[PDB]
Amino acid sequence: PQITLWQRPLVTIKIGGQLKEALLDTGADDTVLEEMSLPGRWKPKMIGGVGGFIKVRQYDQILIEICGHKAIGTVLVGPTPVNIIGRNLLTQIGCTLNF
Amino acid sequence: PQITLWQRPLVTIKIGGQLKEALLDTGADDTVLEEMSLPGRWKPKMIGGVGGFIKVRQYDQILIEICGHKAIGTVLVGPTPVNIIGRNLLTQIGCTLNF
Ligand SMILES: Nc1ccc(S(=O)(=O)N(Cc2ccccc2)[C@H]2CNC[C@@H]2N(Cc2ccccc2)S(=O)(=O)c2ccc(N)cc2)cc1
Ligand SMILES: [Cl-]
Ligand SMILES: [Cl-]
Ligand SMILES: [Cl-]
C-alpha cells in the first residue's frame, strides 16, 4: 500500500494472537505496545520523549503481522498512550518514506 | 527521495535562514522544533508524548524548507528531544509511507 499522512497512519496488527490498531511511526527507534502479555524472557528499559520517560519491558524475537506482512523483532511493552510500530519492524516489511 | 529506515530518517531543514537537522516523524501530528526565535505572535498548544502532555508555543504560517521542498504552516517550539517534522508538513511536501 501507499499510505497518506492526511490522517494518522493507523493499521491493524496481529501479535500474541490479538488484533490491535497501531501507528506506523518513523520517529520511533523501537516498537512499543500497550500492556499485554508476551512469551519469554524480558529486561527493563526506559524510553522517553516530550512529557518524560516511561519504564517498559523489552522482549526480543517476537513475531508480529503488520498489515498482512510478517516480521520478527524486539517489542517493548508498557504504559504507552498509543500502540507504535517503530523502525526496528518497519524495516522488515520494506516500509519507506517517499516524496 | 525514497528513505529507508535502518537509521533515523534525519534530514536537513531550513528555517529563518538557518540549516538544522530534523527527524521525519510520521507518528507526530505536529512539527516541533527545539527552542529558537520565530517571528510574530504565538498561541498556546498542548502536545502529548509517551510520558504525558506539555505546553509548547504555536507559530502559524511559518516558512520552512524540508529536504529542498517548500512548506508554509504551523511550527511548534518547545523542549523536544530532537527537531521533528510531523504530518502537518509531511503532507505539504507530498510524503507518503510505502510498502
Ligand atoms: N525509543 C523510543 C523513544 C520514544 C518513543 S515515543 O515517544 O513513544 N514516540 C511515539 C509516539 C508517542 C506519542 C504519540 C505519538 C507517537 C515518538 C516517535 N513519534 C512521536 C514521539 N516523539 C518524538 C521522539 C521522541 C524520542 C526520540 C525521537 C523522537 S514525542 O517527543 O513524544 C512527540 C510527540 C508529539 C509531537 N507532535 C512531537 C514529538 C518510542 C520509542
Ligand atoms: Cl529488533
Ligand atoms: Cl531495504
Ligand atoms: Cl499547518
Image (cartoon, coloured by chain):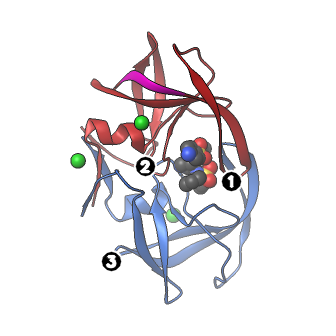
Chain colours: A red, B blue
Q: With respect to residue B98, does B82 lie above or below?
A: below
- Output the chain of dot 1: A
Q: Secondary structure beneath disc 2?
A: loop
Crowding at dot 3, Cα within 10 Å, few <14 / some 14-19 / many 20+, comes out as: few
Ligand 1 within 8 Å of disc 2? The answer is: yes
Q: Which residue is drawn at 44% across and 76% down?
A: B13
Ligand 1 within 8 Å of disc 1? The answer is: yes
Q: Quadrant of residue B32?
A: bottom right
Residue mark closest to the camera, 3 vs 2: 2
Crowding at dot 2, Cα within 10 Å, few <14 / some 14-19 / many 20+, comes out as: many
Instruction: Check disc 2 and report the residue beneath it.
Output: A26
Instruction: Check disc 3 and report the residue beneath it.
Output: B68
Q: In which quarter of the image is the C terminus of chain A?
A: bottom left
Looking at the rendered structure, the kind of residue marked 2 is Thr
Q: Residue at x 63, y 22 (%)?
A: A35
Q: Which mark is residue A50?
A: 1
Q: Secondary structure beneath disc 3?
A: loop
Q: Residue at x 65, y 29 (%)?
A: A78
Looking at the rendered structure, the kind of residue marked 1 is Val
Span colored in magenta: A59-64
Q: Nearer the viewer, residue A15 or B75?
A: A15
